[PDB]
Amino acid sequence: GMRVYLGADHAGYELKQRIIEHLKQTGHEPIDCGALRYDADDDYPAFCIAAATRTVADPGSLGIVLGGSGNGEQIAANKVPGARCALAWSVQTAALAREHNNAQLIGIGGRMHTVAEALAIVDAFVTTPWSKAQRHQRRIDILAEYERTHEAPPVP
Amino acid sequence: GMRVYLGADHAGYELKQRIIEHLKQTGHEPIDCGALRYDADDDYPAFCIAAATRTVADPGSLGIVLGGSGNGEQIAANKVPGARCALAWSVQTAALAREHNNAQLIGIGGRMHTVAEALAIVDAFVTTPWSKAQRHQRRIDILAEYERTHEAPPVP
Ligand SMILES: O=C(O)[C@H](O)[C@H](O)[C@H](O)COP(=O)(O)O
Ligand SMILES: O=C(O)[C@H](O)[C@H](O)[C@H](O)COP(=O)(O)O
């Protein structure tokens, strides 16, 4: 049972609403950050920053942000302090985003998948645990430290 | 043109060396930020932050960051102020990254493609122009302002 914050522009709006329904059906708690209706001209950043900000502030939660490709949306979510947003374009990448990257959010492209494919990506994301493996935590900590100071760490 | 900054961990290392060779052959100037050798245990953030920082600082340059999926790498690159790093998993997504998101960088997963698929992705990325269309520029500006202030833009 996961709480999931969702954000989308117009290009991801229709898939977002379908995902919200699916998440309800499969025992989860979706929270819609908008867009709340289709608006052809609307701008992705606000919705993605909102979902990402709320996700980071609510530990244990996850997030999903949607656009055409999903890339603008993961980019915007990733600007939020503490947020790690993968682009999920397959079951495997959704799974690995959790397992390796402890990603609290994924971006999905509404123009990229069938509904069946998208929901499969969503299922993998909400059910795959974070592995807690040492090397992954080490890498996440390194990135977290860069985010704290914006001082580029030295390369080997 | 052009200068292309490459960063990879061990999981994207062999693909990175292949991409560098390909970019030389296609008339570009690849710049290797590391890893310079295969180290099975190495940590992606430093290489990706290096690539992203150098790309954002170098007008007209692009950047490519590689890992297993590419997702930890685009996340790290996106923590760099001013950087927009998409995850490119196809020719279409590489092209749209440039066209819509004006991404200076893409992440590619070394575990996700054949070399031929990966090089097609690279070609699309380095040859597809930024559209300069109004709505895309507006969205990038909104994100840049959030990076500047951390004031979450209002949701409609
Ligand atoms: O993920 C994406 O494809 C992006 O961030 C936007 O959704 C896309 O540029 C919208 O394109 P539009 O509907 O404005 O043509
Ligand atoms: O792009 C990704 O797959 C990630 O950021 C790392 O490359 C991945 O977790 C490395 O996995 P490892 O080789 O340590 O199993």
Image (cartoon, coloured by chain):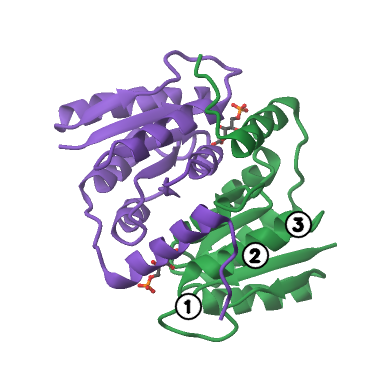
Chain colours: A purple, B green
Indicate which quadrant contains ligand 2: bottom left
Quadrant placement of the N terminus of chain A: top left
**Dot 1, how many residues are within 10 Å of its Cα: few (below 14), some (14-19), or many (20+)?**
many
Of A27 and B120, which appears nearest the observer?
A27
Quadrant placement of the C terminus of chain A: bottom right
| Residue at the image point whose x is 50% and y is 85% from the top | B38
Instruction: Please identify the quarter of the rendering in which residue B22 is found.
Output: bottom right
Left or right: B91 with respect to A20? right
Asked if badge 3 and badge 2 are on a common chain, one would say: yes
Q: Chain of mark 2?
A: B
Q: Secondary structure at mark 3?
A: helix
Separation of residues labelled 3 and 2 (CA atoms):
10 Å
The residue tagged 3 is B57
Of A122 and B137, which appears nearest the observer?
B137
The verdict on label 1 being within 8 Å of ligand 2 is yes
Q: Amino acid at mark 1?
A: His
The residue tagged 2 is B51
Asked if badge 1 and badge 2 are on a common chain, one would say: yes
Which x, y percent locates residue B144? 65, 37
Q: Amino acid at mark 3?
A: Ala
Q: Chain of mark 3?
A: B
